Amino acid sequence: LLKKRAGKSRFVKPRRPYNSEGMTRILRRYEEDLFCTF
Amino acid sequence: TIEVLGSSHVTNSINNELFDPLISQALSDIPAITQYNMHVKKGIPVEDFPKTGLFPEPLNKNFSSNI
Amino acid sequence: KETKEVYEGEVTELTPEDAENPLGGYGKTISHVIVGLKSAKGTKTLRLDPTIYESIQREKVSIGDV
Amino acid sequence: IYIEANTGAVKRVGRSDAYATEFDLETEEYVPLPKGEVHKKKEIVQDVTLHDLDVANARPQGGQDV
Amino acid sequence: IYIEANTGAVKRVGRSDAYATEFDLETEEYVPLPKGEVHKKKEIVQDVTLHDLDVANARPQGGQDV
Amino acid sequence: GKDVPFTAIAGSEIFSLELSKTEALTQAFRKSIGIKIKEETELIEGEVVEIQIDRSITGGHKQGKLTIKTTDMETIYELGNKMIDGLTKEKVLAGDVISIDKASGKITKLGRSFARSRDYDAMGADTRFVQCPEGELQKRKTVVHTVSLHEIDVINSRTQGFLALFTGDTGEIRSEVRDQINTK
Amino acid sequence: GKDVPFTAIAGSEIFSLELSKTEALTQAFRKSIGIKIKEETELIEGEVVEIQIDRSITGGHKQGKLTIKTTDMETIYELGNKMIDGLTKEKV
Amino acid sequence: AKKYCDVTGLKGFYKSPTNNIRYHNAEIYQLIVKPMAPGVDQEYLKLRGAN
């Protein structure tokens, strides 16, 4: 097994992290708009 | 640097003049999570914040530093 | 020369209407703002953006003002 | 980033290329990770005149104070 | 400390010698107790020219700190 | 012809209370040499689908995402401060057709294609109708533009040189700036 | 010798643009009279043998031991919080 | 509490790190504090009860 192992055996990049904590939000959809405040 | 040997009042006044917190807060900005901690978690209103963000914008990203 | 399209008068009501599905971690998510205006010989209720309510709060617009 | 401990000046090199590239809209440039350790001491050979030192001390810019 | 009653000016001299042994090394300067009484009163005479009163009100930038 | 500078001045314009005669003559000499700079840019033309804008409480730190589409693809971009400032001026409302220049940072609303029924009493994009663009979303283009040497010295002189290009408050630029600009 | 003011100017150096001639002459006159003041200060000049720093998780209370010496003596000092801050800055 | 020199009773400015004896100046440290025998430092510290 050792002689057979030695002789025969010897992608999309991820996006940036998006951190929006304690911050307001404006969303503009096709049908309705939002304003998430505090 | 101006130094006077044997007095802490001159050092305190010099450190107050060089790093005046009102001006140094005016020429910068508070972090967003800190602002969320002041306004929501602590009950401080928006108008009671110190005035921030008075620094003028540079022309480019390349013009913002000497390095 | 220019043309101006304006809406002016005394405020009758000022209601920020909430959304059907508010988002978590937030508070009073607004879908639109209903403002009613009154002037000489005319009243009219409006339907506004969610954004202008921030300007209403910054300009300190209470009830009864013009 | 690049923090110079002599004066406290910080240079933003740009986004790291370990993450995605084409999803931006602000004409940024992408730089790999710097070789060697985080803390470094390097030797830069500089040429200067005495008038440069005179105008640097006459109009003080470079510190982090007011 | 040093408090002037008429002007409200407050001056700090430093910590006292009774608290000089709270640490072996400290950055505070240590002064002895004042020998005289706490309250002192004194009659003084001030001489001011009219140009002093003119220049004390004609500052274009504004007032200055003490 | 165009793209060749022609600085025509009279003789009495040299004498000034802010600049010396040599400095004014140096600026008049340096206004007559053009630098033609070639740049690479990316043009994006697509229908706006989704706009998410996250701002701080004081309105200082602004970031967000923009989902844009054409008839063939679908792309989500990350936005900076200047791009959100461009979007907030002459407001786009999720269904318009806009144009994007990466190197110039220009926002140009071509029009509106969605034709929404429900519209708030204010706003109102009686923008001319336009079809949704098709094909490639992103296209590369080589652009060229001319600047003068004097504008380069005024811009590199201090922090706010672009204002001094119009106000004329460029008082006695030092020689080291001109040597470094010549070398660059 | 040294310690005695000597102001050597030229005749063409007082025709200024921000100062009058009499004001420049007054400054050149008053640059040549000095005040001699003697004062005393106390200093600790020594060679650092060992610095021991005890720190908390949140940085509330700091403890410090400083073994410092000359070629003649040797001593150990307990350090307060502001001396800990002044020794961390300008790293000794 | 005030700190005093263990040998002379004067104002103690320094403390030796080996035997923990407060001393006054350099020559007190050289003549007494350094070459002292063991068993003497505990008796010096017995007066203020520091052993």
Image (spheres, coloured by chain):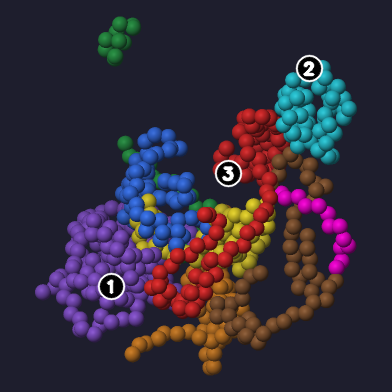
Chain colours: A green, B yellow, C orange, D blue, E brown, F purple, G red, H cyan
Task: Tell me if mark 1 has few (under 14), some (14-19) or many (20+) residues whose alpha carbon lies within 10 angstroms of its own.
Answer: some
Vertical arrangement, residue G78 with respect to residue F165, above or below: above
Which residue ends up furthest to the left in the rendered image? F1
Dot 3 and dot 1 within a common chain = no
Question: What is the secondary structure assignment of the residue under circle 3?
Answer: loop
Residue C35, quarter of picture: bottom right
Dot 2 and dot 3 within a common chain = no
Is F9 magenta? The answer is no
User: Where residue E24 sits in the image (x, y, percent)?
Assistant: 74, 39
- Horizontal arrangement in the rendering, residue H26 relative to residue F49 (left or right): right
Chain of the residue under label 3: G
Question: Toward the viewer: F137 or F159?
Answer: F159
Residue H15, visible in the rendered structure = yes
Mark 3 or mark 1, whichever is nearer to me: 1
Amino acid type, callout 3: Lys
| Magenta range | E28-40
Q: Main secondary structure of the magenta part?
A: loop
| Label 3 sits on residue | G89
User: Where residue F148 sits in the image (x, y, percent)?
Assistant: 22, 68
Amino acid type, callout 2: Ala
- Please give the name of the residue rendered at 87% of the width and 30% of the height, measured from the top-left corner: H48
Quarter of the rendering occupied by the C terminus of chain F: bottom left
| Label 1 sits on residue | F23
Residue C9, quarter of picture: bottom right
Amino acid type, callout 1: Glu
Question: Toward the viewer: D6 or H33?
Answer: H33
State the CA–CA distance, disc 3 to disc 1.
47 Å
